Amino acid sequence: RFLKVKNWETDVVLTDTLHLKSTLETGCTEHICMGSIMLPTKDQLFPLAKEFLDQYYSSIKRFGSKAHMDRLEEVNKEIESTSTYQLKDTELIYGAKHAWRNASRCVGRIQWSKLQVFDARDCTTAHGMFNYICNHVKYATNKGNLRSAITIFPQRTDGKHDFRVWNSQLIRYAGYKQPDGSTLGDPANVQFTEICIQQGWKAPRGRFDVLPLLLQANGNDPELFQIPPELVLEVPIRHPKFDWFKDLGLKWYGLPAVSNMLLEIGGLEFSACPFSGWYMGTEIGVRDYCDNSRYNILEEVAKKMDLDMRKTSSLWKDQALVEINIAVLYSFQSDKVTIVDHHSATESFIKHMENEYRCRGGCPADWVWIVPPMSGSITPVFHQEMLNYRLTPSFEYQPDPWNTHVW
Amino acid sequence: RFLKVKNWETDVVLTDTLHLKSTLETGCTEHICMGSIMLPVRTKDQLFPLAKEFLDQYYSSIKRFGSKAHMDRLEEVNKEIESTSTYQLKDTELIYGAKHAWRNASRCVGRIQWSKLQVFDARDCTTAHGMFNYICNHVKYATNKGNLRSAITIFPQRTDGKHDFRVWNSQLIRYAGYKQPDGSTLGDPANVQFTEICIQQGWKAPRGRFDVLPLLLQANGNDPELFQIPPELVLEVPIRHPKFDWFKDLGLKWYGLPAVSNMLLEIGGLEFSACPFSGWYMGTEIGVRDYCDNSRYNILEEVAKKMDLDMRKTSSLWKDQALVEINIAVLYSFQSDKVTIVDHHSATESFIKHMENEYRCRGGCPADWVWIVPPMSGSITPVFHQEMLNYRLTPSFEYQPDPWNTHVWKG
Ligand code: HEM
Ligand code: HEM
Ligand SMILES: CNCc1cccc(OCc2ccc3ccc(N)nc3c2)c1
Ligand SMILES: CNCc1cccc(OCc2ccc3ccc(N)nc3c2)c1
Ligand SMILES: C[C@H](O)[C@H](O)[C@H]1CNc2nc(N)[nH]c(=O)c2N1
Ligand SMILES: C[C@H](O)[C@H](O)[C@H]1CNc2nc(N)[nH]c(=O)c2N1
Ligand SMILES: [Zn+2]
């Protein structure tokens, strides 16, 4: 019931008790592990509220205080009356930071307590949402000195007045299918690139077109908005050794801002809560550039390096992958845009893990996601045993809006 | 109940029914996943149904389920159990068992090869000298002058737990590791503790960088004995790089035959505590893990210096760069010497085909993503994007504690 995790490179052993406070389900059973599966009313509400307020008031050293008891009293009143309740700003901020702190798949959590929270619960329209989103982008970007931020729109009421950002990220490049057969731009965004066009967007049908925002307020039909180009910081990609690299004509944006997740706090659901930090190099160079179902330019780059692409055993893909990732990092660093390499980030995470075991009794961590997509075993997280479990507040997945929206 | 797994790169969806045949526990619960945990004297009482379940499996595979041969065998085993408290497997059953233990090894990416396994029955063995002979023959057969052949040698099963056969070595062929008084390590750091035991047992160490360790062999629960593998049986490969001439001067080499010898083979409730098996290497095992793990030979820096890389900031990815070239050199050396090896792209590509075939013909393929994904260049191999289900089927290979921690010493 008290679980131990071992690091095999250092022999360090941590003891986890935090998992006992876990409440949601993993998808695993004692007969089967699902660790590599990507996607596994009033009476329901008050225990959920109670649980949250319990941990909040414990965190400020007023567990069992009159304020705690009164707040519990007040929230219970509000629930029986209104069939929901509203979070105080302090509780909202706490809940957002803790959803990040609890995100078992995030390697960047050493930063969790420095999150800038923007309360947008007074928002009523898509133009309103647009304004808040623009403010978020400008603040987070900070001319290249990136700052973590989340903007929180009004909570779900009854599933009919949902606020939703339809983009998966605030900033992404368009993808177009050809008659020629292949794909121009980003293949992951083909379906969304088409819905925007199916909606009125006029595409420059280029290789790297910044997608428009598609914003849904209060359950209404979503509207297109173009993000002011001066708010979208981009980094041209060059290599510090290969002069022909620049000629490839690649660039990427500095701000990773995830916008399709659901934030759960005290039973309350925030369906629109775009958040942003800064990139780890491999998200762009390994996943975005080199994935087969994405920009997939490994071959192109290998050619210009004139590697023997004859047999897989020359490891030409491995060689190209590395140079690319060197370029991504070189480019952002040169341009004073915040980026972290996978070595630094995983080293930071090990330190964060040890902090959390110390000050909290554990740290839920999903190895399958924490270990980077290249050079896995030369990073310290590879040799680290991790326990995965779900804590709340939390970020959850939710269905794509176009599959659900009562149109 | 039916379970779906998706390949996110191809959108191929597969359906698993085989997991229903699973009995053994995973470690996971509904509230925790222990997916990344490395490591998560039997009575006639529980032996009966274990035997029966194995025999049901075996007779189904040969399409004789419920036959008179099936039923008689069941009666024969049942009688042997209540009489002698254990039982003996037929040769056919033993071969089926060993092959299926491999087929079921969810952490093994080489399983496309599972049906081609040479099974050596060493159950008539009684002494350590006899164990040495069987192991020598295994190594000679498996090596085959570089044209590697998968093999397993199986020693007598456990009885009362007091007469165990054990190979004390973790692998049949490994290099010694020596801790120096100045805190540094000569040879393979992973083998320091085992090297000490050998030396204590009387092994005269040459105390070099690549000394092949002696075999420490325990028959019938007796104290283990030292044997040196004849050097002509130990195929080794000098590591060079195809473009870098300075690489040979690093002085590296590795042995050709990976042969794991510390696992336990469970078949029909019987436990085979000594069952060394061998295949051939995936290049990254040597190049990534053996040479580049910080806890092993750890030659990354020396290689990076000789490449004249920017070693000042990790963001130069000097470590990643050196890692690739070391792995290129490993593959190049083995191919040049015509010693069987597989790169991680070929091996993972083959595993995917195997897994798809298994889902079709068998209803599933237990697979441990954490171990199947290779230790470098993970996302550019097809297994990275493959969802996998991990569960435990018998027959199986299991971990067991190191013998030096459990052995009762005789003298
Ligand atoms: C500040 C620098 C940050 C870094 C370097 C970072 C790093 C990462 C990386 C590499 C992943 C895996 C992404 C993928 O492979 O698709 C991830 C996932 C995730 N991140 Fe972080 N992150 C940062 C900030 C944040 C912030 C500010 C939040 C929320 C407030 C957050 C919440 C999450 C969540 C919920 C996931 C997993 C989503 C899922 O379940 O699929 N991260 N992070
Ligand atoms: C024929 C070529 C083979 C290849 C290329 C191969 C490849 C691999 C690799 C790369 C691993 C991971 C090892 C590690 O990272 O420590 C592994 C694990 C494993 N292999 Fe295979 N293997 C082969 C043959 C065999 C054979 C013949 C057997 C048994 C008869 C076997 C049984 C296992 C088992 C039980 C594991 C898991 C060990 C553990 O859980 O720690 N393999 N294999
Ligand atoms: C495509 N992978 C599935 C999927 C679906 C929805 C969200 C998501 O999040 C990835 C994610 C989330 C937060 C991040 C924060 C910072 C960062 N550099 N990357 C981050 C990446 C991942
Ligand atoms: C060091 N990791 C823990 C541990 C403990 C005991 C055995 C073992 O086996 C790894 C293993 C097992 C079988 C293999 C077969 C072929 C091969 N190329 N590598 C193989 C590697 C691994
Ligand atoms: C903590 C973690 O389970 C451990 O380091 C594992 C990770 N994946 C692995 N994968 C393989 N193939 N071999 C290993 O030894 C390991 N080690
Ligand atoms: C099949 C597998 O679950 C899928 O490819 C996962 C694996 N690990 C990952 N790890 C990270 N960080 N991000 C991902 O998108 C994925 N994808
Ligand atoms: Zn699990």
Image (spheres, coloured by chain):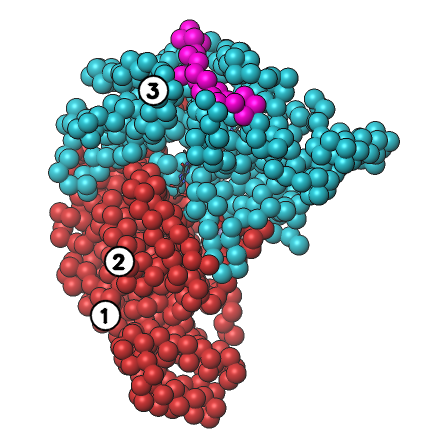
Chain colours: A red, B cyan
Q: In this figure, what is the number of numbered marks?
A: 3
Q: What label does residue B199 carry, if any? A: 3
Q: Residues within 10 Å of mark 3 (few under 14, many from 20)?
A: few
Q: Residues within 10 Å of mark 2 (few under 14, many from 20)?
A: some
Q: Residues within 10 Å of mark 1 (few under 14, many from 20)?
A: some
Tell me residue B163's x, y (percent). 57, 27
Quick one: B337 or B89, which is closer to the camera? B89
State the residue at coordinates (49%, 78%).
A159
Considering the numbered disc 1 on the image, is that residue within a helix, a strand or a loop?
strand
Chain bearing tag 1 is A
Which residue bears the numbered disc 2? A355
- Highlighted magenta segment, given as a residue range: B214-233
Q: CA distance from mark 2 to mark 1?
A: 22 Å
Q: CA distance from mark 1 to mark 3?
A: 61 Å
Magenta stretch contains residue B220: yes
Q: What label does residue A116 carry, if any? A: 1
Chain bearing tag 3 is B
Q: Amino acid at mark 1?
A: Gln
